[PDB]
Image: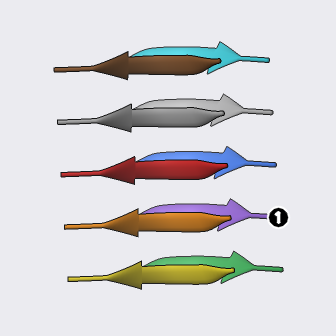
Chain colours: B brown, C cyan, E blue, F red, G purple, H orange, I green, J yellow
């Protein structure tokens, strides 16, 4: 699981 | 599961 | 942007 | 930006 | 930036 | 699990 | 920047 | 697990 | 910059 | 586990 990336 | 990405 | 997840 | 996850 | 995760 | 990256 | 994780 | 990177 | 982790 | 890098 992870929050976010760009 | 993950939050978001762009 | 987001609050939370599980 | 995000709050939290598990 | 993010708050926390586990 | 990880928070974020760019 | 982030607060904490485990 | 890790916090963030760029 | 970040606060802490374990 | 690690905090961050650039």
> Dot 1 falls on which chain?
G
Dot 1: few (<14), some (14–19), or many (≥20) neighbours within 10 Å? Answer: some
Where does residue C1 sit, x and y in percent of width and height? Answer: 34, 19
Where does residue I3 sit, x and y in percent of width and height? Answer: 60, 78
Where does residue F5 sit, x and y in percent of width and height? Answer: 30, 53
Pick the quarter of the image with the N terminus of chain B. Answer: top right
Position of I3 relative to C4 (above/below): below
Does residue E1 appear to the left or right of J6 in the view shown?
A: right
Residue that appears at 55% across and 21% down:
B2
Image mark count: 1
Q: Nearer the viewer, residue E1 or B4?
A: B4
Residue on which disc 1 sits: G6
Residue that appears at 79% across and 17% down:
C6
Residue that appears at 47% across and 46% down:
E2
Badge 1 marks a residue whose secondary structure is loop
Position of E3 relative to I1 (above/below): above
Pick the quarter of the image with the C terminus of chain B. Answer: top left
Position of B2 relative to J1 (above/below): above
Does residue G4 appear to the left or right of I1 in the view shown?
A: right
Residue that appears at 48% across and 62% down:
G2
Where does residue E3 sit, x and y in percent of width and height? Answer: 58, 47
Does residue B3 appear to the left or right of I3 in the view shown?
A: left
Residue G6 sits in quarter: bottom right
Q: Nearer the viewer, residue B3 or C3?
A: B3
């Amino acid at each position: 699981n992870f929050g976010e990336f760009s």
